[PDB]
Image (cartoon, rainbow over all chains, first blue to last red; front, side):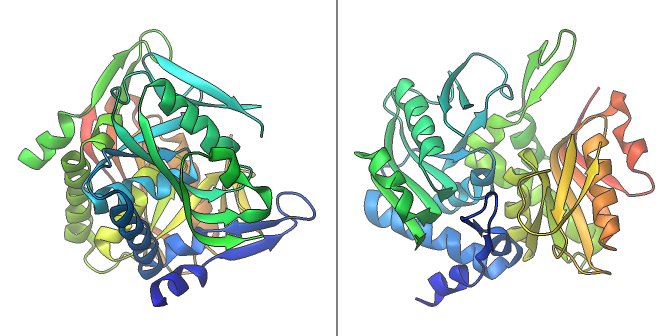
Amino acid sequence: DSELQLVEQRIRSFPDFPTPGVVFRDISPVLKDPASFRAAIGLLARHLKATHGGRIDYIAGLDSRGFLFGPSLAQELGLGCVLIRKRGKLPGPTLWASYSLKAELEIQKDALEPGQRVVVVDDLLATGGTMNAACELLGRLQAEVLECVSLVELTSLKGREKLAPVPFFSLLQYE
Amino acid sequence: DSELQLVEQRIRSFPDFPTPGVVFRDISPVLKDPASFRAAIGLLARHLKATHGGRIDYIAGLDSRGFLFGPSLAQELGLGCVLIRKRGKLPGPTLWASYAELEIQKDALEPGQRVVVVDDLLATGGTMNAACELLGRLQAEVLECVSLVELTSLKGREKLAPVPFFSLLQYE
């Protein structure tokens, strides 16, 4: 897959960041190369249309690296994008949810109406703590989370299991 | 400008946030309405092409609300997007500047490359001024800073001189 290769070629791996023993998979070069970014968005959009047809109402992007992809993916799909932010940033009435990093994500109580169907996007799935918190917040708005997606998944951390029974899809997988 | 109206009509204004007496201009509804987001990006893109022609090499997006616009703006211009983050988030070697601290990878840009910085909102201009400094340390040329919203009574534009500034919408 030439397009998937365009994305994989622009992942930069940094050993021992942020702590010794791990490897940080940096999506920065994907953003810097417009052909790579277009490829990433297209692959995610194509997967989502092939899987949900027209059932998706909104994309939810996760603060902060998910913000890089959410609006472009939403645009490609003809949809709006709603924001899930670190706590303290959003005006009006909010809900929030913890997750070990303790950190907290937040959403405006009026971000979605009950029954609206959403796909959550972030750059990278690791432990799945952040994505889990996002799922909880959306569920508390009585939104239906159709799927969570990322560019990169770290399979040995088993974040995917943690989101079950919500489906997950990543472009690329590393241990 | 009906395109501009599509953006302005989706700004939501919250009094007394984050502190009493200030009005918060919430751009969330612009993102939630795909026609509004498209208009915003289109208006910014057209301004930048009309002003700089082919001179721009990259868009730089400021963490975090700048990340919402920078990639889409870059894509509309056929450009890549480099990232300026809060300190501690980028791997590898970085430069940082305090204003809170911002950070950029040392190889984000090469000397002589020309960049336009984007953020959602210009207030005091502290964040944007720091970003300009960092880019300068890479010997990049900042052509312009742009935002969706500018709060004119805070005189952030004057902080950025002599770098030009452009906003879609202005509020006292």
